[PDB]
Image: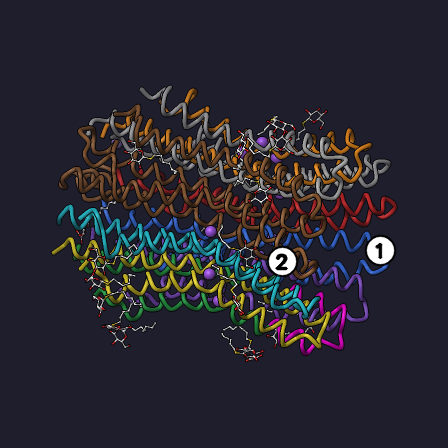
Chain colours: A brown, C orange, E red, F blue, G cyan, H purple, I yellow, J green
């Protein structure tokens, strides 16, 4: 307890003294940093693809073009979760839909932060899709005549792996542009 | 600074946190995708069975992503706290 | 700060946190899906056995996802605190 | 607010956090499921042995998931704090 | 709301956090389960030694889950702070 | 009111956090159990040396789990702040 | 005590959180370094091709690390909130 | 409250957080235990060289666990802030 | 001027958070070290190339740890917020 | 409570958080240790070169653990904010 007010009432009073927009901006900054945590995923996954690509080229150097092609295509797919988070952060930085709002400061602030929190889901697809890229590169190095079939199955599976990244992006966009709480 | 607004604010956060469940299927299904590609490459003749097994297994891996989404959507559009 | 409101608000948050449990089965069952796809490609004639085993094991892997969902549904629709 | 409403609210938070433990068995048992499916496809005649081992080990992996649920249930329905 | 209420409140949260420890044995024991099932498929005649070794190792891996449980239970029913 | 009970409340929180360390040995020792089981199946006649090596290595992996438990015990029963 | 101070404080913390993104490339590129070292050992005559491929892939894996840094630097040195 | 008591409370929290470092050595040394046990099973008369190498590498892996312990012990028993 | 202390306090927290980036290179470079040691055992004649490749890749995996360090050092010794 | 005490308190938290970096080298060096032990078992006569490679790579893996320690030590014993 802080003096007499419980810590919750203390924190609310503390936050209450500021113009609402400053509070909203502050929580946006947090939302912004949190969104970027998604970048862990493509880093792990694309690095895996890099390793499998290096291994495959070592085994079959005359096929480096096909190996590298699928490594890069698959890695491009893995990048999307990272791009999405970057977009959300950039929106919260430079086109913030909460700051110029009439509604409750608590709701706008929480929503700003919540938008970034949701984007953390992007770790999953980035990691998984990058793993898939590396296996694609590996398989193509072993059997380049199957590169088309390997690419398609890799892309199908990568698409399935994307959905929870999309669900999260959808929740953030709802908080930002179709908020039921306002 | 009504209690109602504080319920709604924490509902936003709860909803956002529910989406972190999505990390799991992303990784797991990625693994499934990579094994599918590896397997189709090795035995193109079995690709129909391989792809069907990968998708079936991937559907199962999806459920806890859906459970998180459902909780988020409940907090957003069918909140029981108000 | 009305006590009822603070209880409800924190219930929303804890409900979201409980769903983080869902990360686990998503990873594990996706691994299961991948191994299943790999085994079917290797031995198509055994795919009935492979899939039954994959599914049985994935079902066991689902339970802690369900436990998380249950706690969230309790907080939402059968809250013992009010 | 009354001291017990605050305790209740955090109890809801503490309950949700307890369920994070469930991430563990989800991953681990999923791995067991994948290895089980792989071994069955390799040697279907030994599937009785493979599956029994898989389940016994998975049963062990379940416990810390149960431990978390118990703490959650204690906070929800048998709370020592009020 | 007394300071004692705040202690109980944070004990409820500390207890939940303690259970996060449970993630580890869940993963590791699941891995042990998978390797055990793999080894059994490869050599069913050796399953008694394989299983005993698996359960011995898993028992060890269980301890830090118990440590977390012990800390939670202390916070819940033998709290040194009140 | 303030001060002493705030330290005790945060100590409860610190103690729980300290147990998160337990995640590590749970994973690592479960991996060791799996490799040990696998090796025993492969070379039953070497199982004594296999188990010995596994347990020695597991013992070492336990330490930071214990360092964590120690810090929690200090916060609970030998707290230097009060 | 100004609202400006609250913005800056949150920006300081948010900049720090953004750098957590850097965990990913550190793991992934370390994996690439390991596979490249292994590949060169097996096939030293392909060393130039193996390394160029490793570095191209590692360059791609770097980007989300750079995105995090850029966001941190914006929050520090070109903050749009003030 | 007195600022000194706020310093002590946060130090308790910081002490617990520092122990999270222990997750790493638990995982890594567990891996080494597993590889050591595997290698001993395969090459019984190389056992001493295997174990020595495993222990040497484990000792190195221990260090960041110790660094965390030291920071926590500083916070607990040799705190510079008061 | 109280607000400047608030900024300073949060910068200290932000600086620590930035160092979490260091988890990544620790894991990745340890993998490279293992693969390098394994490759050297397999083909000792190639060790200078193996190691050179291992270190080159390790240098790349280092960058995001350094980015974290830099954000920490900015918040500590060249802080633009005060 | 003086602003200084708030800075010292937050610095204690920041120092704890900085140590989280240590999770990484613990995992990575433990991996190196296991691969080194495995390589020595396979080829005992190459053990001096294997161990030297292992330790070199491990030393590189240590640095971001050292970076975190340094940030914590700064916050503890050379704190620029007061
Ligand atoms: C995610 C896509 C980023 C675009 C990068 C273009 C790289 S271009 C790339 O260069 C390689 C050098 O080894 C060639 O082997 C390969 O055939 C070529 O596609
Ligand atoms: C990220 C979505 C990728 C969609 C599939 C690629 C179109 S088709 C694909 O084109 C690639 C680049 O031209 C080539 O690697 C390959 O030869 C060709 O089949
Ligand atoms: C490219 C992937 C990310 C997709 C982002 C979807 C939202 S895009 C978003 O749309 C708003 C509509 O009002 C615009 O005001 C805003 O400028 C724009 O950034
Ligand atoms: C919504 C899916 C977007 C990505 C398309 C993936 C590759 S295209 C895809 O390939 C599959 C596997 O060979 C086929 O079964 C399917 O007919 C075809 O549409
Ligand atoms: C998240 C991974 C998704 C990768 C999908 C790449 C192909 S997306 C797109 O899908 C269309 C079907 O609607 C196809 O007709 C078209 O060829 C394809 O480019
Ligand atoms: C998340 C689980 C997704 C479940 C998808 C159900 C069938 S989806 C359907 O399945 C075909 C089977 O070959 C694919 O080739 C095709 O591209 C796809 O559209
Ligand atoms: C991990 C699942 C939950 C813990 C295990 C509870 C067993 S569940 C229970 O088990 C019985 C025999 O044990 C079976 O006869 C029955 O089909 C099944 O429902
Ligand atoms: C962390 C608890 C276990 C610490 C290791 C206990 C000694 S274990 C013992 O130590 C001998 C010393 O010469 C080694 O040579 C031998 O290989 C080993 O078995
Ligand atoms: C590092 C752990 C030190 C433990 C010190 C021995 C017990 S000391 C003593 O133990 C009792 C526990 O219920 C209580 O009277 C009290 O909380 C505690 O200070
Ligand atoms: C945008 C792509 C950045 C990474 C490019 C990967 C191959 S870059 C490659 O690096 C080698 C390192 O020794 C040099 O020998 C070679 O001249 C150079 O082209
Ligand atoms: C790549 C940008 C980050 C590294 C360089 C720091 C930005 S340069 C920056 O510019 C401003 C003066 O014009 C001030 O904020 C500050 O004194 C100065 O460091
Ligand atoms: C590339 C994204 C930005 C990363 C570096 C942070 C901005 S750097 C900073 O930007 C200021 C904006 O007013 C300039 O006035 C100043 O000269 C410049 O140093
Ligand atoms: C906390 C784990 C400490 C490691 C367990 C005791 C081994 S101590 C370790 O042992 C190596 C192998 O004999 C020696 O060569 C080395 O000098 C020594 O540091
Ligand atoms: C790497 C970006 C941050 C670089 C900050 C410039 C250091 S400047 C210098 O730094 C010393 C410690 O390093 C402090 O003791 C001293 O007060 C400070 O002025
Ligand atoms: C690679 C170096 C990047 C350093 C980040 C730009 C900081 S700019 C920085 O502003 C500080 C304000 O105290 C001064 O201490 C310092 O001398 C000045 O250069
Ligand atoms: C959501 C976080 C809310 C945190 C509010 C509690 C910090 S209130 C804190 O009080 C201190 C001494 O009175 C001052 O030094 C400091 O400037 C002020 O922010
Ligand atoms: C402080 C913990 C250090 C962890 C690393 C173990 C020491 S490894 C150490 O480092 C040298 C390179 O710097 C190696 O070449 C050499 O083999 C060895 O003396
Ligand atoms: C923590 C940094 C460790 C040193 C990294 C750069 C060392 S430089 C490196 O040093 C090795 C032995 O010292 C030699 O094997 C190698 O030829 C030399 O290039
Ligand atoms: C990356 C290394 C940065 C430098 C290490 C921390 C220096 S911190 C610096 O140290 C000076 C000498 O001890 C003190 O006089 C001063 O008060 C303190 O701010
Ligand atoms: Mn009362
Ligand atoms: Na999905
Ligand atoms: Na599922
Ligand atoms: Na389960
Ligand atoms: Na267990
Ligand atoms: Na243990
Ligand atoms: Na240890
Ligand atoms: Na990238
Ligand atoms: Na170390
Ligand atoms: Na890097
Ligand atoms: Na390093």
Is A47 on the left or on the right of I76, as rendered?
A: right
Q: Position of residue A31 (x, y in %)?
A: 32, 42
Q: Quadrant of residue A149?
A: top right
Residue at point 56% right, 61% down?
G54
Instruction: Classify 10 Å Cα crowding around label 2: few (below 14), some (14-19), many (20 and above).
Output: many
Residue H17 vertical position relative to residue J33 in the rendered view, above or below: above
Q: Secondary structure at mark 2?
A: helix
* Residue linked to disc 2: H30
The circle drawn on residue C3 is none
Residue J69 horizontal side relative to residue F51, left or right:
left
- In the picture, measured across the screen, residue A174 lies left or right of residue J57, that is left
Number of residue marks? 2
- Quadrant housing the N terminus of chain C: top left
> Which residue is at 37% across, 46% downward?
E81
* Foreground pick, C66 / F67: C66
In the figure, E54 relative to J71: above or below?
above
Q: Position of residue E35 (x, y in %)?
A: 73, 47
Which residues are drawn in magenta?
Answer: J34-54
**Residue drawn at point x = 59 percent, y = 53 percent:** A68
Task: Please say if the residues under marks 2 and 1 sit with CB atoms less than 8 Å apart.
Answer: no
Residue that numbered label 1 is attached to: F44
């Amino acid at each position: 307890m802080i003096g007499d007010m419980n810590i919750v009432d203390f924190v609310i009073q503390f936050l209450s003294q500021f113009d609402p927009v400053d509070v909203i901006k502050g929580f946006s900054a947090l939302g912004i940093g949190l969104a970027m945590v998604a970048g862990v995923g493509p880093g792990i996954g694309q690095g895996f693809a890099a390793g499998k690509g290096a291994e495959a080229v070592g085994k079959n150097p005359t096929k480096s073009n096909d190996i590298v092609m699928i490594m890069l295509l698959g890695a491009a797919v893995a990048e999307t979760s990272g791009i999405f988070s970057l977009v959300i952060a950039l929106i919260l930085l430079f086109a913030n839909p909460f700051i110029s709002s009439t509604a409750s400061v608590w709701i706008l602030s929480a929503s700003a932060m919540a938008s970034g929190i949701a984007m953390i889901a992007g770790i999953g697809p980035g990691t998984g899709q990058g793993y898939a890229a590396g296996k694609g590169a590996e398989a193509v190095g072993i059997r380049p005549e199957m590169k088309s079939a390997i690419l398609r199955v890799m892309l199908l599976g990568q698409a399935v792996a994307q959905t929870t990244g999309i669900y999260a992006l959808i929740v953030a966009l709802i908080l930002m542009y179709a908020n039921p709480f306002l | 600074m009504e209690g109602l607004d504080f319920i709604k604010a924490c509902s936003a956060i709860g909803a956002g946190i529910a989406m972190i469940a999505g990390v799991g299927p992303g990784i797991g299904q990625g693994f499934a995708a990579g094994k599918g590609a590896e397997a189709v490459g090795r035995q193109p003749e079995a690709q129909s069975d391989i792809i069907r097994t990968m998708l079936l297994g991937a559907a199962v891996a999806e459920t806890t992503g859906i459970y998180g989404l459902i909780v988020a959507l409940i907090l957003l559009f069918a909140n029981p706290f108000f």
